[PDB]
Image (tube, helix red, strand yellow):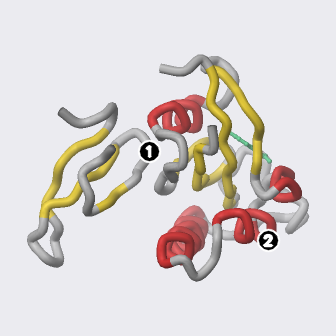
């Protein structure tokens, strides 16, 4: 009954049922609502183990994988609360050059991007945002725009 990747779970805090997606790492209280191409933006946070530990922000990326995840979780909280929008955080903080285009990567098909990125991208519906998505490049928040 649920879309690809989506499973039902129990909240450790409240005992209330929630839904999470094991492909996108999305999680929400609400029950969840294949194209050749999708369009996505992302916000990338790199760490010391990233394939290329360097960006326009920081010549030498030193942060730990754990500290990168803390950063990602913080940005997700601010996006979800409405305190900051995705585009503004991507522009300021993404370790990808796409930061200069508010994180926009344009449109792409399967067979183009790192696999965990692609799979998360194609499991989102238009408008939906992922949780933390891990690739060899670092940790991503992905917004599907088309
Ligand atoms: C999957 C994916 C998407 C965008 C990306 N940007 C980068 C970078 O090194 O700037 C890696 C990467 C990987």
Closer to us: 124 or 110: 124
Rendering coords of residue 103 (x, y %): 75, 53
Report whether 20 appears left or right of 132. left
Residue shown at 45%/34% (left/top)?
123
Asked if the beta carbon under badge 1 is closer than 8 A to the nearest atom of ligand 1, the reply is no
Q: CA distance from mark 1 to mark 2?
A: 23 Å
Look at the numbered disc 2 and give the secondary structure of its residue.
Answer: helix
Rendering coords of residue 74 (x, y %): 54, 76
Report whether 47 appears left or right of 12. right
Rendering coords of residue 142 (x, y %): 59, 50
Q: Residues within 10 Å of mark 2 (few under 14, many from 20)?
A: some
| Image region (quadrant) for ligand 1 | top right
The numbered disc on residue 139 is: none
Asked if the beta carbon under badge 2 is closer than 8 A to the nearest atom of ligand 1, the reply is no
Look at the numbered disc 1 and give the secondary structure of its residue.
Answer: loop
Residue lying at the far left of the rendered structure? 15
Residue shown at 68%/57% (left/top)?
43
| Whether label 1 touches label 2, CB < 8 Å | no
Rendering coords of residue 78 (x, y %): 55, 77
Closer to us: 100 or 55: 100
Q: Residues within 10 Å of mark 1 (few under 14, many from 20)?
A: many
- Counting residues from the N terminus, which is met first, the one under dot 1 or under dot 2? 1
Residue shown at 33%/44% (left/top)?
33
Residue lying at the far bottom of the rendered structure? 83
Q: Which residue is mark 1?
A: 24
Q: Quadrant of the C terminus?
A: top right
Relative height, residue 59 to residue 7 (above, below): below
| Image-quadrant location for residue 38 | top right
Q: Which residue is mark 2?
A: 92
Relative height, residue 118 to residue 10 (above, below): above
């Amino acid at each position: 009954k649920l879309p690809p990747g989506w499973e039902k779970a129990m909240s450790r805090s409240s005992g209330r049922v929630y839904y999470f997606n094991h492909i996108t790492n999305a999680s929400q209280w609400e029950r969840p609502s294949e194209p050749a191409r999708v369009r996505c933006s992302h916000l990338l946070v790199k760490h010391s183990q990233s394939r290329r530990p360097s960006s326009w922000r920081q010549e030498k990326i030193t942060r730990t994988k754990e500290e990168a995840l803390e950063l990602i979780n913080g940005y997700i909280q601010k996006i979800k609360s409405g305190e900051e929008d995705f585009e503004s955080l991507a522009s300021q903080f993404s370790d990808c050059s796409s930061a200069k285009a508010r994180g926009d990567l344009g449109a792409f098909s399967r067979g183009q991007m790192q696999k965990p990125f692609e799979d998360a991208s194609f499991a989102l519906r238009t408008g939906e945002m992922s949780g933390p998505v891990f690739t060899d490049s670092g940790i991503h928040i992905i917004l599907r725009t088309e």
